[PDB]
Image (cartoon, rainbow, N blue to C red; front, side, top):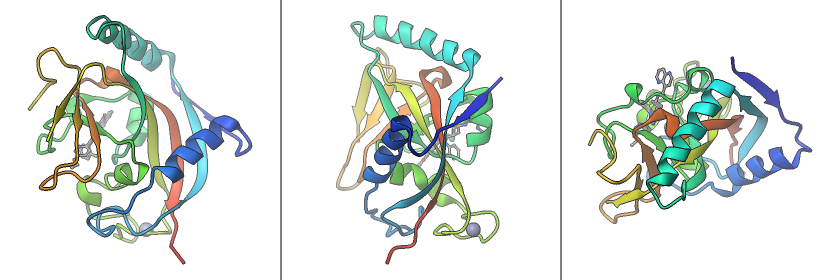
Length: 206
Ligand SMILES: CCOc1ccc(-c2nnc([C@H]3C[C@H](NC(=O)c4ccnc5cccnc45)C3)n2-c2ccccc2F)nc1
Ligand SMILES: [Zn+2]
């Protein structure tokens, strides 16, 4: 029972999500090996995802977390990348499909940097790239990120199967022998809602 509402490029709501995606782009340690080489996207479509079932199951979990974190949800708008976006918008985030070899264990990963989420769109480390050209830096094939409402609650700072005791999420941090950029991880699908579905291409520089 999911409905996509196509947003006009002249919508302030569109422009807000567009601005956030473009501005949160960073240079990457791997020289774009995983995500491709770019400093800007081609923003084709931004659609608002609408599902009462998935929305109600989010708000319900958000309430519980607030009561366990001094009446503060710790709600953040964050980008999500994965090969499973089409499923997520229909059946919601599902921890049961989490990759156990992840750096912070079997969780659903988010980022405050759109360019980081991009790296995971065609699998872990961009996998074998786009299906058509088998190219991680493909400027041709259309990509999809989710821009999600995420309840982080009491987030454990680090650098596993569920959140540490007393906590509701993990915030990964830049270590000289570790991460360059921030990660955010939940171990429960109901703690995130995919509010916006963004269709885009990475754009060739020069
Ligand atoms: C160092 C980088 O390591 C990472 C980065 C991101 C993630 C991650 N975060 N979230 C995901 C996906 C797997 C979750 N799947 C669903 O929520 C889901 C929901 C509904 N239906 C599905 C059907 C098939 C697969 N997944 C689903 C979301 N993934 C994910 C899981 C497996 C493979 C690639 C991924 F991006 N895991 C590890
Ligand atoms: Zn391609």
